[PDB]
Amino acid sequence: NKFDLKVTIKPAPKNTMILEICTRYRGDQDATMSILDISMMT
Image (cartoon, rainbow, N blue to C red; front, side, top):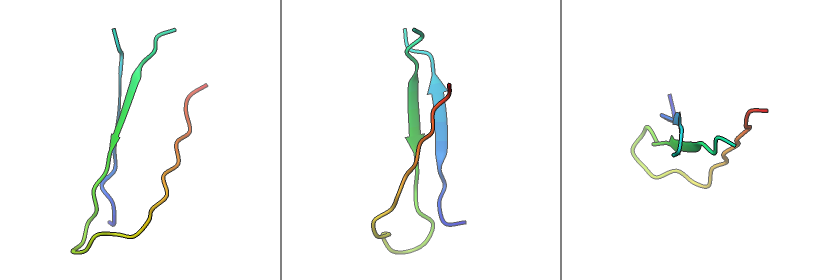
């Protein structure tokens, strides 16, 4: 319930793709410091 993370991957024109992740909070006040972890494909 807390977050609303969204992840997308697109091919950029050795494929060299582009990854974009966007997040937002669910509540009423700004959150404190947060941690984000990313693990990529082989």
